[PDB]
Image 1 (spheres, helix red, strand yellow):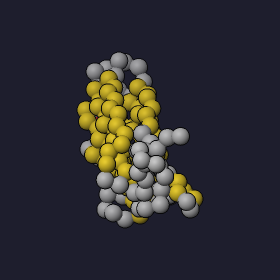
Image 2: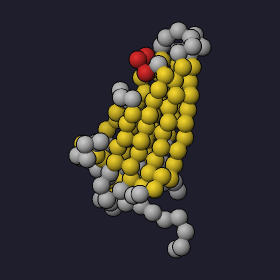
Image 3: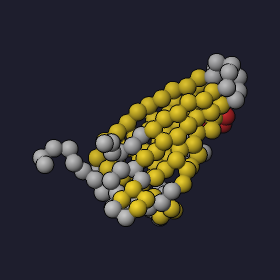
Length: 126
């Protein structure tokens, strides 16, 4: 093939801003390889499992693999339980090896009701 085929190390970045104090945001982190579920690593470069979830309880976030993977997934949800006009922004970006290959952004504001929403950013599709 001589087209868009790059795999191996998968890396991901998340950001949040706005009312971080009063928004839970939780992502299941994971992937697979030629060898079962792929290992994931934290932003200290150290492995921490082959499945888990992490709540965004930082300003910025990222996770990475080692070699042997064929995607990484970062799929999650938001909630809030506060007054109206609490605004939020989320930026969710996926990378492989040395390129960016996926991004979306999302924005939420409380209207008076419970806030709930969901999102997902995978670095490979079929």
